[PDB]
Amino acid sequence: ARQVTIIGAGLAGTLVARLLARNGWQVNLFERRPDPRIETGARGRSINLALAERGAHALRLAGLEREVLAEAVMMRGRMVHVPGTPPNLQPYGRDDSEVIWSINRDRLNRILLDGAEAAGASIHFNLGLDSVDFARQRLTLSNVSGERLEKRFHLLIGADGCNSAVRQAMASVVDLGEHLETQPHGYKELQITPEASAQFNLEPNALHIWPHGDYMCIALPNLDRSFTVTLFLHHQSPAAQPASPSFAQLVDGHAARRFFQRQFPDLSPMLDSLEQDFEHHPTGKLATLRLTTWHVGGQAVLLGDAAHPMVPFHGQGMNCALEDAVALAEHLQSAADNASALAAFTAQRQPDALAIQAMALENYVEMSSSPTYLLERELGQIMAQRQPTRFIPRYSMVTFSRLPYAQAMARGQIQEQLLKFAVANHSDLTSINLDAVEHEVTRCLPPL
Ligand SMILES: Cc1cc2nc3c(=O)[nH]c(=O)nc-3n(C[C@H](O)[C@H](O)[C@H](O)COP(=O)(O)OP(=O)(O)OC[C@H]3O[C@@H](n4cnc5c(N)ncnc54)[C@H](O)[C@@H]3O)c2cc1C
Ligand SMILES: CCOc1cc2oc(=O)n(CCC(=O)O)c2cc1Cl
Ligand SMILES: CCOc1cc2oc(=O)n(CCC(=O)O)c2cc1Cl
Ligand SMILES: CCOc1cc2oc(=O)n(CCC(=O)O)c2cc1Cl
Ligand SMILES: [Cl-]
Image 1 (cartoon, rainbow, N blue to C red):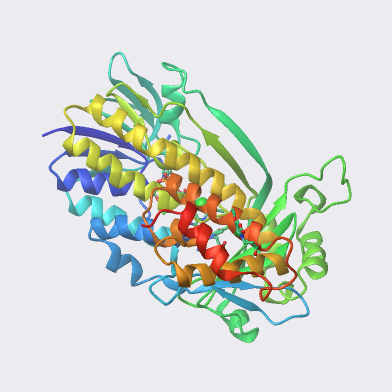
Image 2: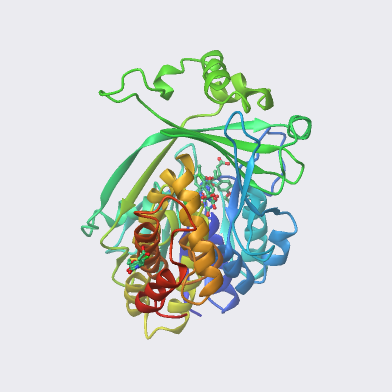
C-alpha cells in the first residue's frame, strides 16, 4: 500500500485524504487546529462559503454531496441593494438547477473529516508542521506549546492553506518563482440575526450585494435565517484620496456604526451587533500568490490555497481547491510513479489556477460597480437563447460547468469583446442587429 502524509485537514486536504484512503493508500493527515467535531463550551461563529458546480461535483465523486447539500441554502441570484430603489434580483442561471449553495464552513469541514476517517485515513490534530528535511525525508511538527514530534514521510501533500508551511519548506530547497500581488481591501465579518433579517424582509435564497465602488458589503444566508455580512474596504486611504474610506479611519465600533449609517443606510439597521462584531472580529487580509512550481520531484506537492491563494470575489477558492483534490487523487492513483503524478497534476492545474485568479480579480468591479452592464447582459441572454452551445456567459461557465477555467476565461474574453462591440455606437437594444451579433458568435465561438 502506497503511503502519503497530508498537512492540513481543511477542505482540499480532507477530500484528497478520503479519495486516496478509499483507493487503499495509507493516509496520515496532520492538522494544527483541534478537532472541530470535539464539542467544547467555546462560543464560535458561523462563516459561510458559496459552493458551486466544481465543488459540488468533487463532493459528488466522494459520495458526500447529499450530506453537504442537506444543510446548504440555495442562492438563486444576486440581490443588489442601492438606497432609494427596491432590491433587484439578478438570477444566476436559467432555472433552479443553476444555483449556488451557501454552506457553513465548519459543518462542511466536519462532514469531510468524518468522510476521510470512514475511508480509512488517520487524522492527527493539534500538530502544526514547522519544518521539512527533504534529504532525510523527515518532518517536524509541534503543538501550540512547541512540544516537537518528528515523523518520517514518503509523499508530502501541502493542503495547509494560504500561509502554507509546506510551501515555506519547499521554497528553501527549490526556487518556487513566487509572485505576490497584495490586495488593498481588508475584510470584516458582521452578523444579521434571524429576527432582524425577517423584520427587514431580507431574501434568504439569494447572495446579497450593497455595492459602493471602492468598497462593498455582501451577505450570505444561513439555514436559521441569520446572515454573515462581509465588508470589503481598503486597509488604508491612498495618497491621491486621503479622505476616502478605509479601516485605518474606523478607530472603533462607534466609528464603524457612523460609516454604515452614512454609506450603507438600508444595511446598518439590520446589524444589531455591528459595534461588537467590528471590534472583536479581526480584519482579514487578501492577496493573489502565483507560483511557477508547485512540487519538489516526487516528494512534495501543493494544492488549494497552499498552491494558489486568490482574492474571494468569485467565490471559487474552495471550489477550485476541491477540484484540485480530485485531480491530484486521480494523477496519484494512476501514474507510473509519484514524480510523474506531481509533474502531470501541476501541468494540468497551473493554467486553470492562473485563469481563476485573474477572473476573481476582475469580478470585484462587476460586483461593486450600471445601465450599460445590464444592456450587455440583456444582449448576452438573447445570444445565450439563440446559441446555447456557443454563447455561455462567463459567470455560468465558471460557476455551473466544469469547463477548464482557462477555456472559460478565453471564451469569456471573446464574448465580452463581441458584447462591447455590438453595444457600441447604439443608444438602445432595438437599434442593434441581432442576426449580425449571432453571426460573429458562429464565426469566433466554436460549439461545446
Ligand atoms: C472572505 C473569504 C470568502 C471566501 N468565500 C468563498 C466562497 O464563497 N466560495 C469559495 O469557493 N471559496 C471562498 N473562499 C476561499 C476559500 O475559503 C479557500 O480557498 C479554501 O478554504 C481553501 O481550502 P484549502 O483546503 O486549500 O485551505 P484551508 O481551508 O485554509 O485549510 C488549510 C488547513 O491547514 C491547516 N494548517 C495551516 N497551517 C498548518 C500547519 N503548519 N500545519 C498543519 N495544518 C496547518 C489549517 O488549520 C486548515 O485546517 C473565501 C475566502 C475568504 C478569505
Ligand atoms: C479540521 C480543520 O477545521 C477547520 C479549519 C479551518 O481553517 C480556517 O481557516 N477555518 C475557518 C476560519 C475560522 O473558523 O477560524 C477553519 C475552520 C475549521 Cl472547522
Ligand atoms: C464571503 C463570500 O464572498 C463571496 C462569495 C461569492 O460567491 C460568488 O459566487 N461570488 C460572486 C457573486 C456575484 O458575482 O454575484 C462571490 C463573491 C464573494 Cl466576495
Ligand atoms: C467582435 C466583433 O463583433 C461584431 C462585429 C460586427 O461586424 C458587423 O458588421 N456587426 C454588426 C454591425 C452593427 O449593426 O453594429 C458586428 C457586430 C459585432 Cl458584435
Ligand atoms: Cl474565493
